Image 1 (cartoon, rainbow over the protein chains, first blue to last red):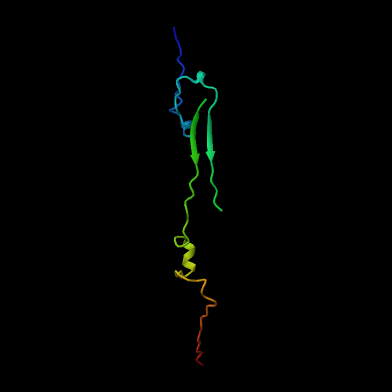
Image 2 (image 1 turned 180 degrees about the vertical axis):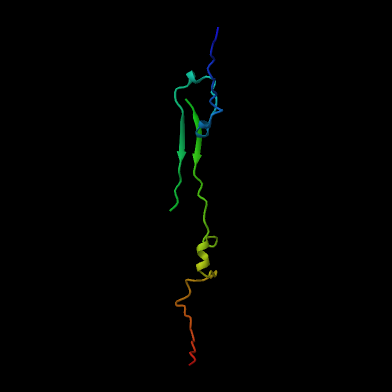
Length: 44
Length: 49
């Protein structure tokens, strides 16, 4: 009997992950929203 | 829901004296400049033949 096994992949061991900050969040089904409030001051 | 951060710009000031523009100028601190009316510089040019 001759079988194949497909090559498995990891997300964090690909060079795609320079474009993402990666924080594992344990219970995301308990979240409604999230927000980031920027406050840009401006010189004149 | 959640706050994930408060991210704020910081204005780093740029002094005129530490620009490289100021090599094109001569900078003197002058205390009372409202008192002055007029400045004046005199040149004397001799021309030999």
